[PDB]
Image 1 (cartoon, rainbow, N blue to C red):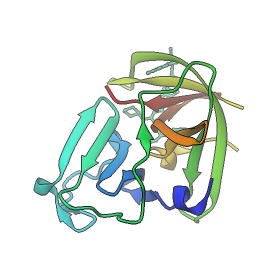
Image 2 (cartoon, helix red, strand yellow):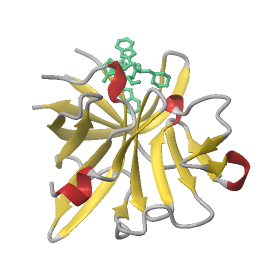
Image 3 (cartoon, rainbow, N blue to C red):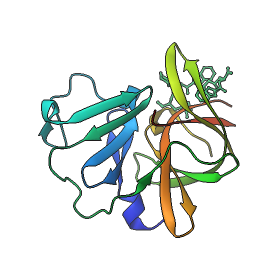
Length: 162
Ligand SMILES: *C(=O)[C@H](C[C@@H]1CCNC1=O)NC(=O)[C@H](CC1CCCCC1)NC(=O)c1cc2ccccc2[nH]1
C-alpha cells in the first residue's frame, strides 16, 4: 500500500483508527477513549459518533484530512477475498497481514455483541492492534471493509458497519 494509505492510520486511545475520507474516521468501539473531551482538537459534542456493535464511525464537523480522497467503505468483503489487515505498531513499524475473509456473523465476544466478518491469517495480531483497517483491491479501487476487533490462536474478527 502507498504512503497515502498508511498515513490514514492513526493511533487512537488504546488502538488505532482510519481516515476513510477527509471528515470520516472509523475505529473499533472498545478502543475509543472514555472521558475524552476532544478528538483531533474537536470538542466531542461537535462530532457525530455512530456505533454499530464494535464498528464506530466518527464524522467531524469540518474536514480534518483534506489531503485524502474518499475511499469506498463496504460491509465486509465477498467470502474468500484475501484482504490486507494494515497493522501499525507504536514503534512505527508497518505490519500488513494477509487474511482470507470468511463468513459474516453477529456473535458475543467477552459479553459484547460484535457484528462483523471472520478471517483467517495466512507475526500475528496483539492487544494494541484493534481499530486497524481491513482493505482489499477491487480492480483499480481500494475498498475498506471494517476494523480489527478480536483474534484467537488463526482467526481474526473484522467488525463491520450495520
Ligand atoms: C484489541 O483490542 C484486541 C486485539 C486482539 C488481542 C489479542 N490478539 C488480537 O488481535 N482485541 C481484544 O482483545 C478483544 C476485546 C473485545 C472487547 C469487547 C468487544 C469485542 C472485542 N478480545 C479478543 O480478541 C479475544 C477474546 C477471546 C476469548 C476467548 C478466546 C480468544 C479471545 N480473543
